[PDB]
Amino acid sequence: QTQVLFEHPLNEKMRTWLRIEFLIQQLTVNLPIVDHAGALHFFRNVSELLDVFERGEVRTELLKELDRQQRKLQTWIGVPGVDQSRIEALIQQLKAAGSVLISAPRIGQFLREDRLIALVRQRLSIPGGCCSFDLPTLHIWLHLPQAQRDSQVETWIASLNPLTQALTMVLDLIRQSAPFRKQTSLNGFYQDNGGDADLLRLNLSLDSQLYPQISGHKSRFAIRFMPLDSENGQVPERLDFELACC
Amino acid sequence: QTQVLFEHPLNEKMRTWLRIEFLIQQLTVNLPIVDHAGALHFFRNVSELLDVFERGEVRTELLKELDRQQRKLQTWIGVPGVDQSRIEALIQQLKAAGSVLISAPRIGQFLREDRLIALVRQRLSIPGGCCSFDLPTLHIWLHLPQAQRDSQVETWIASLNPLTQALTMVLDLIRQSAPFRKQTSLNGFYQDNGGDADLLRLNLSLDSQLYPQISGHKSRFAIRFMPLDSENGQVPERLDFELACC
Amino acid sequence: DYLDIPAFLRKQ
């Protein structure tokens, strides 16, 4: 209510996850697709996902984590106070998402094969290249009955469910595995060890208008708090916040 | 019944103007900004605009067009039947729009020199570089008091007022200088001489299942009506559409 | 020992 949430990947792996998570969230944000603006927002995000998918196989590494989490969960059975009824549920959801992720076809393949999305991607690299005279097919597509568009869009988004499921569950688990430890950075500088951490979470004061500019280093790091307004904003000597290495 | 308006620039000049028209128009489409979706939309359009500015001479070509439209309307001064009161008003508008534009600094100057725009615009050539970990600056900004973002966005849009006004008139006048005329295509093909026209305005019936493939070169254009059914549907012997060479 | 357990794994 009065704190801002900042996250930072401590490794290239978590970096690809946070990105793929964001791009997928965007797809369903401005729905339904009614105007040209909305369409661009959609295909653009879809295109970004297809760009990161080419680089490497996100499937394997995401399965690896689903199992890693299954093991983290089972180490909590027996511990007095643990709601083991909730644990067995998660462990099954992980396995469910595991099979679903395996049985499904190559990630984003259905989107790559789509004729429409293919044409739109070509003109995203061009500043003003996604106009009507550049994308006639898209212009017609935006005049068809609203039901038809919702139909195709739903399908496009559905094809990522296997990825969306495993992804949202991995990150959700990691985010809650570690609590927020209160810290105090003086002079706008912080230095600590991350350890076996994949993610950093920071809750800064809404009124400080400051943001963490974290730098990496092996397993440790370095946070440099800077003001949104570099022309008018200040950085005090005392900065009490909340950190959490996940 | 149900039509679809296709517009095709007959030169690089008008092509740029339609692009800018689209981008400018976009800025005020999803106001006010509240979340990452609305912000990125805005900041991205502002970027494509700036990219368009530095790659062409818009202020020059636009000041010349205003002069042309002034001379064009002047020839109607004194002509019987013409409403002198309307023309004079129009002339003074073009005279004032050109004056305002010519007295204002370089187009996009304010936006291109803005702290936040510069930051956001940098992280656009990257797939997921617009997240909360790659763009902390944008994250806090989306939490500032509304009146503040409102103010910023306002002054940002206003910095383009000299352009937006002159551009609107030019495009308006151009669209008004040539009415739509019924035309017939044979075997999904059409061709004629454009002459001194900067814009093609084509109205096609949605239930034609056809999309116009408008090509341009020198003083003549060629329309090719192609089925949406990817060569699985067929092209009618004759197709009745509307065409206006503005 | 009991607070060392993640809040989401902590109930009855």
Image (cartoon, coloured by chain):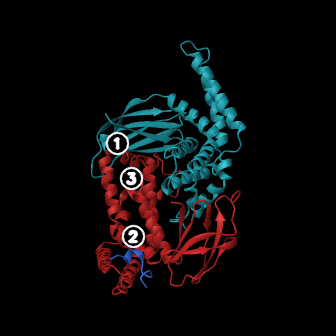
Chain colours: A red, B cyan, C blue
x then y, percent, for residue B45: 54, 51
Specify the quadrant of the image occupied by residue B185.
top left
Q: Do labels 1 and 3 share a chain?
A: no
Which of the two residues, B139 or B222, is positioned nearer the viewer here? B139
Q: Quadrant of residue A243?
A: bottom right
**How far is the residue under mark 1 from the one under mark 3?**
35 Å
Answer whether labels 1 and 2 touch (C-beta < 8 Å).
no
- What's the residue type where badge 3 is placed? Leu
Q: Which mark is residue A31?
A: 3
Up-down: is A229 above or below A68?
above
Q: What residue type is labelled 2?
A: Thr
| Depth check, front residue: A7 or C11 | C11
Q: Specify whether B140 is left or right of B209.
A: right
Q: Which one is in front, A173 or A28?
A: A173
Q: Disc 2 sits on a residue from what chain? A: A
Kindly identify which residue carries mark 1.
B188
Mark 3 belongs to which subunit?
A: A
Q: Name the residue at 43% across, 30% down.
A: B180
Residue on which the image places disc 2: A168
Q: How crowded is mark 1: few (under 14 residues within 10 Å), some or many (20 or more)?
A: many
Position in image of residue B32 (x %, y %): 52, 47
Q: Gap in Å between the C-alphas at discs 2 and 3? A: 20 Å
Q: Residue B176 in the image: x percent, y percent?
A: 51, 28
Give the CA separation, mark 1 to mark 2.
Answer: 49 Å
Residue at 42 percent across and 33 percent down: it is: B243
